[PDB]
Image (tube, rainbow, N blue to C red; front, side, top):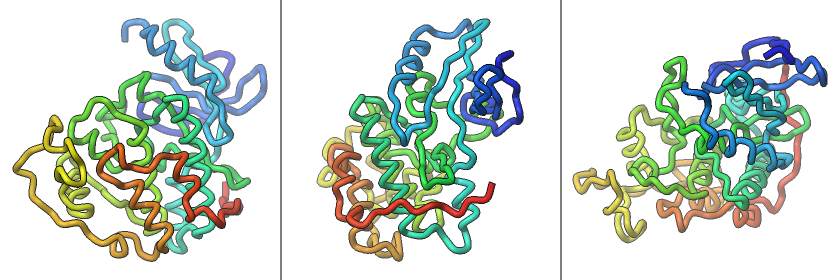
Length: 294
């Protein structure tokens, strides 16, 4: 738009292009996202305008919504790097546990806040977790999945990742809960520790089976109601549960106990963000500053 000088393209998102731009009136650098056609649904207009209100230090702020000339642009506060880049940079040494613990703790604060307002992300992944020089980490694109249903292929045909998707979603459950975000967070948590994706599926069935091989094929004992799920099939291979010590070495007992609670099959059993902040694993959390070169 006119009130903004595009400085550069930051990337090819799920919904559209993302540019770093300078607001000519405030002079502030901002993240400008062009979204996605019949003349923009008023329902999406209302969903988004509600997000303008839930502000938290661990949530990327939605500064403005520009629906000019039947087009939609969302203006978000700008952050320099995402967790995905940072992990690729700390591949050799790994991210230090104190930083891992600080980031998970902040993430859970942002989640607890949104969840208390009944707002889900539904599409958590490293790429939408943004970090700054002072040791902060913020959740980006919160609530947009609800406003604009998460696509299979992005506008540039990029296949959207299934890696962090909760099993109830993969089994065709249509009424997701806040528990889906906890599952995603547990997957990212494991990835930060081992420096390898936990369940890197390349199809919905492959993703489902990767989950089954590790956590064991679910049944009516661990997940009551599972066999009645829309896409559940009695013909699923029956796999045994692997030991967490083998799944996430060298995570200590507290971290492994926490992860196991975030990875419970049954959504009603899965630990809540608010409950997780009180877990012993956070007893010694601090706020270290990351080693990020811009």
